[PDB]
Length: 31
Length: 31
Length: 31
Length: 31
Image (cartoon, rainbow over all chains, first blue to last red; front, side):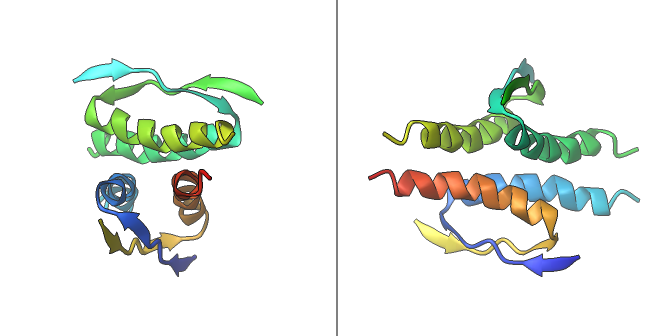
């Protein structure tokens, strides 16, 4: 369990990955 | 709100997308 | 190497995964 | 066109996003 940084270039593509990470984070917030 | 099919070639890559869809689906199952 | 189907519900989210698959497919088209 | 950082927790999940970003980056390297 470690923390990694994902620096991507652009703006819209970064939002796509942000959505996939938004649901995963929701898993940790499944209370 | 419609249903779309994503047919990908390979096997491991398909699992990656499956994980991103596993959390999104978890959002719908946030009960 | 097999073919799998990824049926997702919604419309915008499907586009996100479509982009990640658009680049991967571009890898196979790296000629 | 800007640069954003995606800090995710874990280790395997970060690899998944790294793959989707590996192909996108390959698009910029389509020479």
